[PDB]
Length: 146
Length: 146
Image (spheres, rainbow over the protein chains, first blue to last red):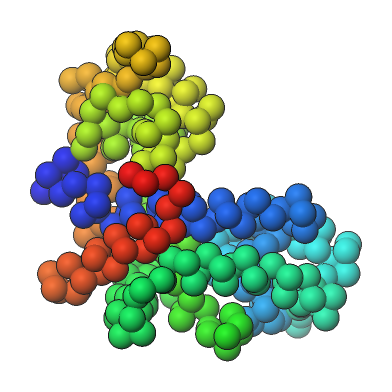
């Protein structure tokens, strides 16, 4: 019932926090290199998969607090990597520019390298099963139904 | 090959970052309540499972940067929740006090609540398979062999 009894290696949050800690740490290394923060790296990645998002929705997908994300977008826009336009819902949507995708495409090899490392010697069947379980857990835990 | 094609929901780091973001966010809510920071919450949890750790090892298990962790332990010790002793390896080890375990035991219900929520309607067999895959991924990705 209690954590001592379960063991850290039988407690999914321990494992996931540590795996993601290393994945994230590895990308952090490339920050000063790309002139990008974590918030910016996350925003570009999400936008590369799906463009034209309201800020609030982007922040939920990216796991970035809204004020932190707004500052990140200000920076990305200043550098020509994203553009923002007002809706008539009196709000704004964010779009990836070709310059922004070019920058994102130079980040992807590090994301891919860590993704491929973490999955070494795990079969396509085990991966499929893994992703299915994660999607169920995300549906279960999430506060926002997206 | 690329993220757009994979889809966010087929990309494990997106899912794990978001699930952990919510798990962690939920615990953060209880911070000001317990007079505890994230670093302290993580340190108590790890120590509750295994006591008498060198700082460096604790920081790796807890996913807390060393200076941040040292400050957290200073606070926990000041409040009688942990104790530190020097080795003859001229370094120090950290131990949970009964007061510290009492505090940790009042944090656990929130950890358990989120753990149980995330696993709702996932069978013991699916969970077993999930944890097996996570352990493989941790072995694959980790820089420190512990």
